[PDB]
Length: 126
Ligand SMILES: O=C(O)C(c1ccccc1)c1ccccc1
Image 1 (cartoon, protein in one colour):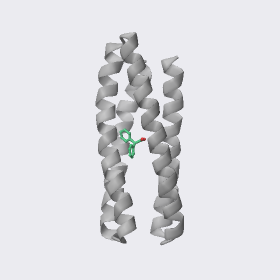
Image 2 (image 1 turned 90 degrees about the horizontal axis):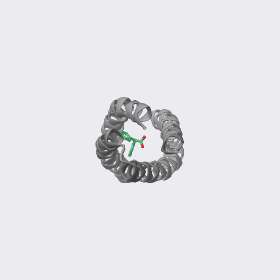
Image 3 (image 1 turned 180 degrees about the vertical axis):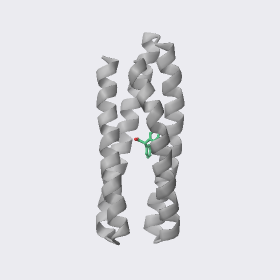
Image 4 (image 1 turned 60 degrees about the vertical axis):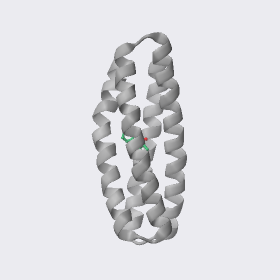
């Protein structure tokens, strides 16, 4: 169902949270080789997460679950914010710009954390 497909999406999001927090520890410890690998894994996860969300949104659309569609439109907009901050974070790492990387990392945490409450309402709605 759409509901189980969103449970799967949610788990992938939780994976990225876990990897993000390991990455943050690695950054604080100055282990750049690890961070690079974690950043690559994060991009794969976010790309997967978005694809699962899009298919779930289109399926709630075809099913006429208007309340779910509204919430998912809002969530996928906030997803793009996350994606833009993430991509800038990656670019700062490549550039060797630790102040920006810190800033984008702090800001991405808050986007994600704030996005968690909408995530939970989508669960109940589907
Ligand atoms: O996929 C997620 O778990 C997040 C995310 C993080 C970084 C880049 C893109 C998306 C997220 C955060 C807030 C709202 C929706 C999605």
